[PDB]
Image: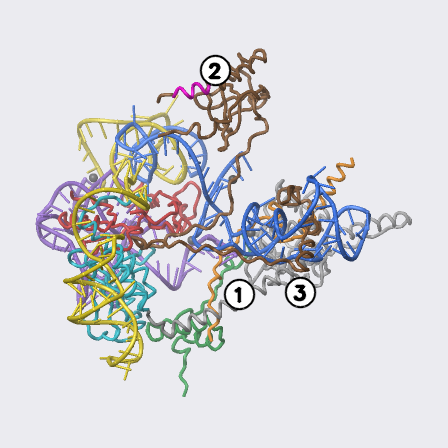
Chain colours: A red, B orange, C cyan, D brown, E green, G purple, H blue, I yellow
RNA sequence: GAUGAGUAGGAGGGCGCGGCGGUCGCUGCAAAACCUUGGGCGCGAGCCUGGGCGGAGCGGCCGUCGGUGCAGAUCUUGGU
RNA sequence: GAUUGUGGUAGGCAGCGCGCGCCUCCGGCGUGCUUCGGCAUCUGCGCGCUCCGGACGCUGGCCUGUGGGCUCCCCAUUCGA
RNA sequence: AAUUGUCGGGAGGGAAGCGGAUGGGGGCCGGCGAUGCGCCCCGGUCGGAUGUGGAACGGUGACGAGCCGGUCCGCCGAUCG
């Protein structure tokens, strides 16, 4: 399948937005939280400190959510759900759900090969 | 009673080109600039030849 | 659609058993439709197989390159068992394309989806051909 | 048919003459008088009906985007004024970097055709990009050198062993070139020696 | 910086669609959106604007 | 073959009528465009001749005044160009209000201003925050050509065509860029409308920098009336 | 076309947890949970997935509900 | 010299050449207005060109390799903290 | 999970950790990165009218007439795809 996307994928930032002091205290997880402290230097945006996410980092709408291969992801749990992409094989790729058994994975892979649908994880459980 | 349907309203914005650099844009905005330039060049050439 | 299709769309566009949604309701949301009479499997009023009196169905029949072309009968909306006028074509792709055009656009049935019907027929034919002889090329060259 | 341009260009896109003088020169008055005070009306050219293209074998599910028309057409590559037939060039890159070679002519593609001569410095008939060359002030007569039959196609790959025909052609071309070179004293040694930068040699100060 | 109030953006809020989930009202709104767009009638514009309003802003008439 | 339904026939007929009326409108527009091109050509020629004549007349008047042994007082400038040179931080109320009324909301924004007792007295209050002088014909022409943006329906549209100017100022006879330049430089009867039509000019930082913006131009700073020397600053700012 | 600072505070759109009414599915050809310098998506809350372990269940979607989201409280219990 | 090509159904807009007349072809020949230089005064059609409604073209290297990529991991360095 | 032992990699002139940019080393990735398409010749299979009959059926109209139409099956020609 030849992807329909033509514009190059541009990422404004590829680093994660790690929570401040999650490196310091084990009990503080990495998942982003906006500081609310009155004196927080991160909240005040002191230079040389942890950066806060904002809408300015937003990805271009034309290339948003596109995988590096040039397609968009769609999770399929069985071969029946695979036929939904029959008319969208140039824009959408299928990823088999993590809980599908190998037996059903083989059938899904065969059907997709018949339908010219890209599978991102076709080698799983083989 | 509906007015005629319109299909050419969503035209892309024309890129702005400085008339001071490229000639065609200047002529489009001011056709007399062609004559002004021609007369200026001819006068300068005549003065240089006379000198 | 025993009631006007616009009302049916207004009702079912929010929810129906054929609606497939994934990745939440943010920018990541992906929507598709499962009903067999949706040519592009798209959740839109244009392609909806539930909110249109005139619909086109194109799917692969069980055996022998047989493609099922069916159109909902306009005067039999209240009779599901006899709602579809089924035609099974076993001839070449050219004849199938001619028949699909004749039954979709030339009679003014649903001219707005002639291209969708032709593309769906081509996809089904290619899928049947590959299913018979298997995969012989990757179709990756642009 | 007019054998000379009616309106010479003072600069790019501006004519030397105005609309009134152009009207006088073009003879629109004469045409009107001959036709009876009215310009002759010419019917629009009839378009050619499109060929009956056979029906497609496949129908794409997506409408591919047709690119918008680009009205700009590339122009021929310019040749620097410092480079003229017979000029000695210094190669700044490639396996022949530093070699001094004679410039013969510019090809259609814009590349420069040069020769060592091959005997003097081992450089055969070759194409060198103008961007990787320095044009010096040394000029050698090349009027007796015939390279008419050599063009961009002469170097085209047919896809290890050099045909003898190319060797013979290079010898024939280089005979006259060496004959011309021998006229200038010390030119043989100059062409047989490579260019190099020594201590306290500044490229931006050398005149070449 | 630019000396503007709220960056030049509007601070007034008005209804742009009905808050109701009545499908028939939605169909009427579509009808009158089309009428307003393709006719430019002041009456149609008033009808469309009033179709958005709340219950207390559509009082009954005896 | 298949009979064409009446609905399709009606749609096709109405589409044909719409196409015909559009073609007629296009033909009329083309003809009027040709006439307008001729008119604007002649008007630009006349304006250039007028500018040259005014310059020659001024020189001759000065020479005649010297010959007679007296003095000739030049006509006072009727037009000014005002550039904001201070930022928007820590603004006094009156200064801020006056700067909004002049349409100078950003540092290095430029606007034309007709000379008037009311306008001059308004500008006197904000003198420390701006610098202004008497623009040249070259300055006005270059500003309008390179950074001239028109205001149509409160939107900023680049003056890439004479139609943009016409749509707003055709009622007053201004239908071309040269007409707008003439109206601005001469401060014609419709100067107000044309000037308001011009979006405030967004000038870049000065190419050679500034001397000192905290001092008046008279003391060696940048603020205040720098009279004919505003033109070189405009060169560096455009 | 214009525009983008934000404590106290207000609001909108979304993410996540556990039930109920429906609907579509997965699972001993291996579910949940947990582990992993495997990979990817989203500005982000989070999400999808490879591999391992585990050995019996679980999830998506539309509505609706709640004892529904922790770094602090000389916070509680347990553990170190 | 430097940064950059956003868009993808338009041959539009503006300016201008060749043919529709001739001669002896770096040019000349007709009617009007001129400051005596010149002038959008005649300036229409067909075919074309351009600084003209947002980048196109050619060549090479490489494709299972000690290759290419990386948001992953451990480190070093400059700046910040 | 805190915390601890062992093995392997790495760093360490009076903290460590951290933000941004590259680089060294490692780890991982083949939708990591294509080999198709068009026009001809040969051979092999499958079907071939606007003709004539049958089966069921549809668009429009008024779930009537009339008009128009596709699918499948059997035949005479056609000798193409
Ligand atoms: K932590
Ligand atoms: K913010
Ligand atoms: K469920
Ligand atoms: K994982
Ligand atoms: K729920
Ligand atoms: K460039
Ligand atoms: Mg600005
Ligand atoms: Mg001060
Ligand atoms: Mg509970
Ligand atoms: Mg541990």
**The numbered mark 3 sits on a residue in which chain?**
F
The boundaries of the magenta stretch are D163-171
Where does label 2 land, which residue?
D121
Q: Is residue D52 left or right of residue F187?
A: left
First along the sequence among labels 3 and 1:
1
Which mark lies nearer to you, 3 or 2? Answer: 2
Q: Is residue F120 visible?
A: no
Q: Secondary structure at mark 2?
A: helix
Same chain, labels 2 and 1: no
Q: Within 10 angstroms of label 2, few (less than 14), some, or many (20 or more) residues? A: many
Residue under pointer 1 = F23
Q: Same subunit under labels 3 and 1? A: yes
> What secondary structure do most residues of the magenta stretch adopt?
helix
Whether pointer 3 and pointer 1 mark residues with C-beta atoms closer than 8 Å, the reply is no
Q: How many marks?
A: 3
Q: Position of residue I79 (x, y in %)?
A: 25, 53
Q: Residue D53: within the magenta?
A: no
């Amino acid at each position: 399948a030849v992807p329909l996307l033509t514009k190059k994928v541009v990422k404004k930032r590829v680093k994660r937005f790690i929570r401040p002091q999650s490196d310091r205290r084990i009990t503080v997880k990495e998942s982003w939280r906006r500081p609310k402290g009155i004196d927080s230097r991160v909240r005040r945006k002191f230079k040389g400190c942890v950066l806060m996410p904002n809408i300015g980092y937003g990805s271009d709408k034309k290339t948003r959510h596109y995988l590096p291969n040039g397609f968009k992801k769609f999770v399929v749990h069985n071969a029946s759900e695979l036929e939904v992409l029959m008319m969208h094989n140039r824009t959408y790729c299928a990823e088999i759900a993590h809980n599908v058994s190998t037996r059903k994975r083989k059938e899904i892979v065969e059907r997709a090969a018949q339908l010219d649908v890209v599978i991102t994880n076709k080698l799983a459980r083989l | 009673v509906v007015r005629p349907i319109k299909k050419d309203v969503n035209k892309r914005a024309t890129l702005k080109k400085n008339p001071l650099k490229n000639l065609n844009v200047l002529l489009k905005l001011n056709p007399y600039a062609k004559t002004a330039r021609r007369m200026s060049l001819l006068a300068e050439a005549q003065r240089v030849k006379a000198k | 659609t025993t009631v006007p299709g616009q009302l049916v769309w207004e009702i079912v566009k929010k929810n129906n058993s054929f609606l497939v949604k994934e990745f939440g309701n943010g920018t990541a949301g992906v929507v598709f439709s499962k009903e067999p009479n949706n040519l592009y499997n798209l959740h839109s009023y244009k392609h909806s197989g539930l909110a249109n009196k005139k619909t086109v169905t194109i799917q692969a029949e069980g055996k022998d390159k047989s493609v099922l072309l069916a159109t909902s009968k306009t005067k039999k909306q209240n009779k599901p068992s006899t709602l579809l006028n089924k035609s099974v074509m076993k001839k070449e792709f050219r004849r199938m394309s001619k028949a699909v055009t004749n039954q979709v656009a030339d009679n003014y049935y649903r001219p707005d989806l002639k291209k969708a019907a032709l593309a769906r027929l081509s996809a089904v034919n290619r899928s049947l051909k590959v299913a018979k002889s298997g995969v012989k090329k990757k179709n990756r060259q642009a | 048919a007019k054998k000379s341009p009616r309106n010479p260009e003072l600069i790019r896109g501006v004519g030397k003459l105005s609309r009134s003088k152009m009207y006088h020169k073009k003879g629109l008055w004469a045409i009107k008088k001959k036709n009876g005070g009215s310009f002759p009306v010419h019917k629009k050219a009839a378009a050619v009906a499109p060929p009956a293209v056979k029906p497609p074998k496949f129908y794409p599910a997506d409408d591919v985007a047709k690119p918008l028309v680009n009205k700009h057409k590339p122009k021929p590559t310019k040749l620097r004024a410092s480079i003229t037939p017979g000029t000695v060039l210094i190669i700044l890159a490639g396996r022949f970097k530093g070699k001094r070679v004679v410039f013969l002519k510019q090809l259609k593609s814009g590349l420069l055709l040069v020769s060592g001569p091959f005997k003097l410095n081992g450089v055969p008939l070759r194409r060198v990009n103008q961007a990787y060359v320095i044009g010096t002030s040394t000029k050698v007569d090349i009027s007796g050198v015939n390279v008419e039959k050599i063009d961009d196609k002469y170097f085209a790959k047919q896809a290890n062993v050099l045909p003898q025909g190319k060797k013979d052609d290079q010898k024939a071309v280089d005979e006259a070139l060496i004959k011309a070179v021998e006229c200038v004293p010390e030119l043989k040694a100059y062409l047989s020696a490579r260019f190099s930068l020594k201590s306290c040699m500044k490229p931006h100060e050398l005149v070449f | 910086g630019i000396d503007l109030k709220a960056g030049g953006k509007s601070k007034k809020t008005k209804r742009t669609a009905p808050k109701s989930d009545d499908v028939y009202l939605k169909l009427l709104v579509k009808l009158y959106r089309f009428l307003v767009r393709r006719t430019g009638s002041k009456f149609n514009a008033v009808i469309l604007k009033r179709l958005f309003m709340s219950k207390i802003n559509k009082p009954p008439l005896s | 073959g298949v009979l064409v339904p009446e609905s399709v026939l009606k749609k096709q007929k109405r589409s044909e009528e719409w196409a015909l009326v559009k073609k007629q409108e296009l033909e009329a527009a083309k003809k009027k465009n040709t006439e307008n091109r001729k008119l604007i050509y002649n008007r630009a020629k006349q304006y250039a001749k007028e500018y040259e004549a005014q310059e020659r007349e001024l020189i001759q008047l000065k020479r005649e005044a010297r010959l007679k042994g007296g003095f000739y007082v030049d006509p006072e400038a009727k037009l000014l160009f005002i550039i904001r040179i201070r930022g928007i931080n820590a603004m006094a109320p009156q200064t801020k209000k006056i700067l909004q009324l002049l349409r100078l909301r950003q540092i290095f924004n430029g606007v034309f201003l007709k000379v008037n007792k009311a306008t001059v007295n308004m500008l006197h209050r904000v003198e420390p925050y701006v610098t202004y002088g008497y623009p040249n014909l070259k300055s006005i022409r270059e500003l309008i050509y390179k950074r001239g943006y028109g205001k149509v329906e409160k939107q900023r549209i680049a003056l890439t065509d004479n139609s943009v100017i016409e749509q707003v100022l055709g009622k007053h006879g201004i239908i071309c860029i040269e007409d707008l330049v003439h109206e601005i430089i001469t401060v014609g009867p419709h100067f107000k409308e044309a000037n308001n039509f011009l979006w405030p000019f967004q000038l870049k930082a000065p190419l050679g920098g500034l001397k000192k913006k905290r001092n008046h131009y008279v003391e060696g700073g940048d603020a205040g009336n720098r009279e004919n020397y505003i033109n070189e600053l405009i060169r560096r700012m455009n």
